[PDB]
Image (tube, rainbow over all chains, first blue to last red; front, side):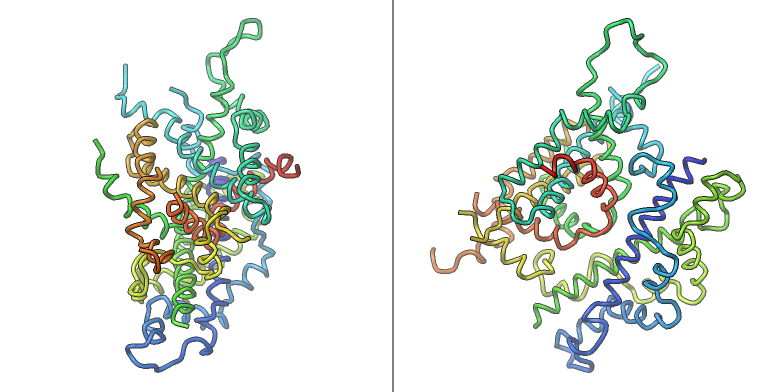
Length: 238
Length: 217
């Protein structure tokens, strides 16, 4: 329950961060603030009319119009809200997964259960997802961090980060070795199992869990678009 | 003119979609609602205290308290706001790049300015998005099946077919009767650059901190 509060806090905080970003865009948008880009009372077959008549502009205008009563930007500012730091960070080591079952799944390896159900009790799917998303987030980091680098420099920098050796070093830093301890442990006196790959996979799976919990609408249009293009391939689900 | 308005319209609409998503999460968060099902405060421990005195909770409680004056969820519904369909879709064939300079750069082939970095970025984001698609769409597939499905989608042959359907051809040619796949990828790179905001920001910052040694090099 204590842990659940921390989990729900970051879910809440990240939603606040998104709201703040979103409202700033809306308040300052060229289409919303003046009539300097979008003329009023233009003819039915003009783009200005089409746009001004959208639910979107009606909502945006209503929001901008209500600032006198509650100014969302000023709300955040007056409470000294910070996006990337909060007082609760003291209680955590790394970004939090909101769903406790999902977090625990990230560390799970290989009467009875269906091969389908054991599949849900294995971090394999999460690892697959997390591997892809680690690559994308790191690619974004290198691309934005080195605006002059060419493809070869970006690829190399990325490779230096996402390789298994580096991920195993991350697992140690994040203390995943303890996460994987349960009832059965090899004593200090007997030769241990090979654990390196297993640790690296957990890192990927943990990122996969962070992604499942955070994926919302930021890239939803791209996502739906890609899913549509992929609809024929996705149909071959045998 | 028309074109600039469409670009700005989608930037605005996507911000409205995110606002609507976030406000719902804020209104319905267990820490904020009255049931107080997690016994925030009642428990009387240091974390309860820390949580209660955050800007975050203070902001959220103010938002909830103002619903009687303006309820953001009702606002959207009362205007029949739809996330994925708008009257402006008339003007477009596929998702819009807000920055026209960025869109143009995506069509500038490698060997000066070129799309090579965008292609790099967009190739990894295509992979991540398709991975998310198959993961969520086949909740029971094993890793092997997910990989087979994904690979059947993101290979250069499929990407070539897409570039054709999308008519990225009629944009690069006119006079004369792998390059094209790279454009599809660069375009996604552009879409990504335009949309990346706060949704994955905490993970991105954490990964960057973890990567600082490597990046300093």
